[PDB]
Length: 171
Length: 120
Image (cartoon, rainbow over all chains, first blue to last red; front, side, top):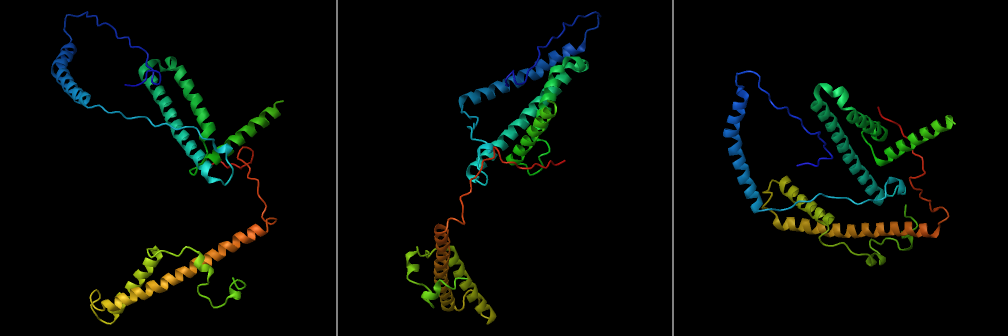
């Protein structure tokens, strides 16, 4: 199972099949034969496997990390804490890449689900995708293949300096 | 470059203050490497005289190993004494003259400027 909020789905609306001809549709008989031949033995096998699972149950946990002061509260050429800051920054980079993957999956699922009405029924998904890729480009882009927290800090300082000269030139 | 240090007690391979250091153990990896060098020298001596390498001259090989391990132990003791002298003199002159060694105020990353060059 998955959490419904992180991967939302609108509720389905399947029409009732209204027959208008006297010819019986063979797809209903095909589905009935499939449920009589395939669904029951697979369900029985899955029930047996679930019983064998419920005989012996054990747990696994999700690892967590506490907060360390980041690269901006570290003395220069001081390795024993700025290493931890770089470590946490790389972990945040990986988690943020997974967040972008989640948003991309949401956008593609919206497009495929809405089909021919994708130009109208998925404005929110495309807007959120545009926002998250704009912020991702403003955070991590053009870092290089040897990226570190110092490079990202320098890029953020450069961006804030450009913002400062932007509001100074506009006032 | 230590011409003014050993001049008070010249021609001393191992002085008295060298006994103040922890002596190297008999299981030092460098000492075992020098013993391996002695064994290799014994093997080479057996090989160059057309003898069975792993059988002949067992007492010769043991003497080679013993002599090499002895001279290696004494040379390692002298090396340890010399480097103790080196870093002791370093720390002593650092302590004696702290005007030429100011304490640098290590600034944090929150205000120092690092130039960023984007890659594209």
